[PDB]
Length: 173
Ligand SMILES: [Cl-]
Ligand SMILES: [Mg+2]
Ligand SMILES: [Mg+2]
Ligand SMILES: [Mg+2]
Image 1 (cartoon, helix red, strand yellow):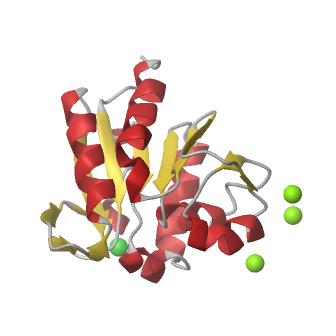
Image 2: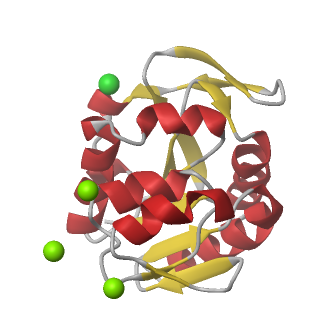
């Protein structure tokens, strides 16, 4: 049931540009087509002004159509941290044996969904309160692969994060 598709979950405004755009280029080059889910259908705009269109509402996501979900951070992500829909997607993908990945502030959604309890992760330095509150173990690394869970510590690690996600996906058929 491999699809060669990756889903992003991110805020429609003020998502972290580098985390999205730099990972997208790597995912595409590797043969993984990407879609964006958010809170409305239309044009999203990053913190730094970069635009992209939102393909899907969270409510329209079907896990069977994707191999992985990627939670993108940025200051706009804070609006999604306590949202039952984004947490619900984290759990949905985990329970369906998909890859669940987050970068920067996106990791907090995963922590709040209780999918990082006793799991080794990394995260944005500023967010370590939330991540530790979710019982995760914070590792001194830019990117951490823990089975099907992949985390990274923010925009400075966007390319390393994407490469790590591709590595996990390419080991699947
Ligand atoms: Cl929705
Ligand atoms: Mg407990
Ligand atoms: Mg709590
Ligand atoms: Mg502990």
